[PDB]
Image (cartoon, helix red, strand yellow):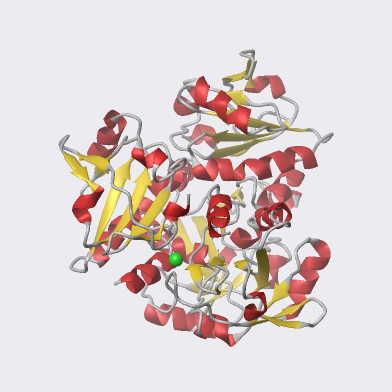
Length: 140
Length: 141
Length: 141
Length: 143
Ligand SMILES: [Cl-]
């Protein structure tokens, strides 16, 4: 029951394509919608166009969209990005805190965190879903 | 609205059992409630039905109820489908305007998870076939 | 039926555009045809709409047509839904009895891919949003 | 590619069972073949596991085989996964490059259906949980 709405989020690390290290708590104070995906996962990639459109649509608002590849190694991820260009800042993560503190066994996975850095939904709806817009608006 | 956020109170609505008797969502206050809103022509809905039944089996004796609620426009195709496909769980049907107007049920499949307190856990809950619904349900008990 | 296997001839049906003019599937013979059968209150159908529109745009000028066919019981919600949601591809609607009785379309969403000769490629085709549909379509072109 | 169109010959690949015995897809020529290519961390993949198993039961004794093929990069999580979740069909694992290369399979879940001549029916078959897969299989078993 650590992951239920209202419970605090759990930090993890992520690398960007250049090498900078960011941690989830850097975005403390914004609404955070996280997309976990991987290059060989069809249903994950099917959601990318909608996650990107959300990014564009809320550019002017206090929410951060984190796309985090969980590919085992970095190279299929970078190889994938070279062929499939993206507008949001891309992250990559094989942080053990994802598996052991977030208990993430499967992807796709979507998470919505509110401004106080509390979980709103540990199991958030997909970015292509009709309701995510209102869910997101509600949270702002 | 902000009224469907986690921690907000569930909204009651009326449904009908296969015998044409009224029931209310409120009758279940005190249990964890997982609702499956579905319809006979909806492939994905009908795809989850095996998993929703198996959840009912798997959690027999825990304080949760599984409500399969048809949103078919008329009861006729619902009862026809049920004659040709038997189910362990008690089946319900609803056309209550409150589904569209208080729960913003514009589309199906729609899954909803409500807590023993009759508060929303997730108004857009994961699907019955997912690993995630198990873990989430385990967490609310 | 064995009538829907790849390489078997497609089955014609009637549909209406927004202005009530009639067309038939067979009018498009000679092109690759990708059909999206959907309805206004089908969540997963409408979630594919952006991708289906993106394919139509991506393949403009190539020898393929994209047919968005609403199977809504009546015309009205279809038309209202379109007023709110402007789509680029020409929209159709159909209650032709053949959909159910020849194509065995019992459930939506449903996607169908037909080749230039008007034979079935895949009567249960991948979804518009999938990576798999583009490679499929290119295969066929 | 054009080589994965219905009616084209299927493409062999090597796979291993939980004991390390080797089998090749082409060994099954003569039977309809429905392949489920999945991995332990792909949620949508294992969402289909029950239905795939239900189908192997529904069609026991008929001229079709059901092949669940883990594409996990390593065998350990696969083996660990089956440990804790029991399964009636014989389980297989593959990392044959023929998958990516010749079958041009870049994403899972992925399902393939092959006819008794070892020709492709659908390289992109419906999911096991779907209502149509059973109509499709039956349609292939009659022909
Ligand atoms: Cl949640």
